[PDB]
Image 1 (tube, rainbow over the protein chains, first blue to last red):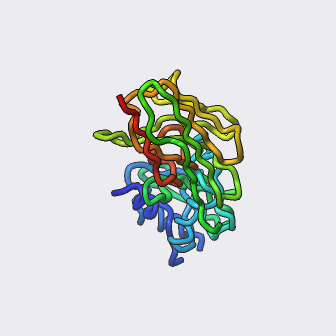
Image 2: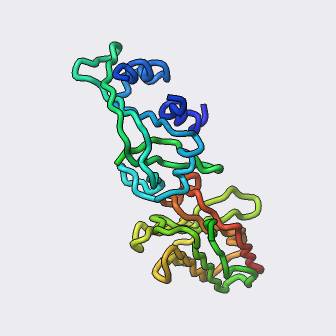
Length: 119
Length: 123
């Protein structure tokens, strides 16, 4: 699996609901080895998300500096584990939002490889 | 100026022991690139990071082979990065590339690249 393809599996849902995160965290394999605690899905075209790597260069939350913030806010869905969630029985709360996405980009072609934050 | 362009100048042919400066100025990007740097690809070798510096003039990193001979600076213009190269050695012969928007000397993290400027150090 390439880094770019892993970002698409974990974070892109361009074609698309309070069960959404429970359905999607399982279908994208994010409950397989552990309950991935927080994960965001983006409901914008893949072209529009890839274009963020040409938008505003900002620091990543860990201090790396190859992150990029979208000039427009985007339709996103935050998936966050519930208080009862415990692996192997993962459970998620779904929250829809409209926020600027921040991604780390790598490669040539230069594309998103990590979803960092929304602001 | 719809396209980002990393304009490279300086470099070229020089005798061993001599000096050159490489200059890079980005145009077409409205904000500040946090990291800029210089990479090179020498004959027979993979591309490597040579020097990089953050927009505050800090986070400065050099390839071990050039520490104490090359000096990177960003104090000469917004999104500009310069490399003073002293005491040049034949093994510094390479295509040098300006890069912007990445992290430290990690090539895969940079998304904007100059076209490449030849530096040739003769004996």
